[PDB]
Every structure is written in structure tokens, then in C-alpha cells.
Length: 8
Length: 91
Length: 92
Ligand SMILES: [Cl-]
Image (cartoon, rainbow over all chains, first blue to last red):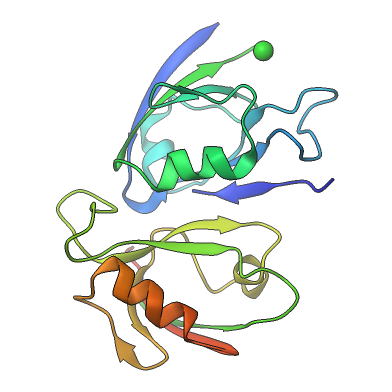
């Protein structure tokens, strides 16, 4: 599993 | 507490970041939900003041994301209407 | 107010998308341009530090897209390989 963070 | 926040995409987009999602390393222990992880110092979210880092995102434009994958929430936020209605939950 | 971003296609996802365009759902009200719409924090775009969400895409590998339709610009971007060169316009 991976940490997911996204700028929107 | 639950709060609705409304944002129009502008020069910085919505101007915040989300973290988490089903199947991803959780943002909080044992809780794979979608959370507001950062707010840009410029941009719509910053001018509105209605979002707080750590807010749980319950729904995006009426679509429940309490169990959503990250990319689904990202699509709801960036691939639909420029105006975004958020249901947010705070502890 | 204008910036170039250079991205090399690799094992790592580019970690960004574009939205908008002529004939498409506007990415922002009253503006049919092409804009960077998302940036994933573990992708090439974020690692480069040269792209910001909301940046207007002016050209892709030298090809003007200031009046492109969305699918045309997406087609241009996927044919920009192995290297993607973007001319970006950013507001204050
Ligand atoms: Cl819950």
C-alpha cells in the first residue's frame, strides 16, 4: 500500500 | 460536526490537497477515508476559509466518498463541474 | 508569469492531468483554456517542482494549444514522449 496525496 | 463548503476552481484550482482513500496507506489509523491534508496559502479554499486541514471529506457534489478510492475522489474534484460542494466532518 | 516545465517519462507516473479546452466543460468559469488540474505528490510533476495546479498550458512540445479542444491536447500530450515540454502561464 502507498500513501496518496493530491493537490487539486 | 458537519459543514458544507462550496468552492469554484480558480487560479490555484480548488487550492487544497486530499489524502487517503480505500486501499491506500491511511491518513489516520485504521481509517482509509478522504481527508483535507493541506490548504494552499493562495487560492479559492484559502479565500473561502471553510476548509480545515484534517477535515474528513464525506461527499463531493453529492457523491459519498467515505469508502472511495483516492483516484475516484480526485476525479470527482477535477473532472466534473468547476463548482465543488463539499460535505466535511470535523472531530 | 510564464514558466516552462520539463518532464521525463520514466518508471514513475507523471502524476498530473490537464482539463478544459475548446468545446469541453470549462475547467474554470468563463475560460476555455487547458489547465493543469491535479498533481499527485509522488509523481514526476510534483518532483520537478515546476508545475502548479491551475497553471494554463500554452504549448506542448512546441505545439500551441491555447485554443485546442481537450481530446486534441490529450492526444498531443500522450504523443509527447519520452520527454514532455510544457509552456505554462501562471497568475499572481
Ligand atoms: Cl465515518
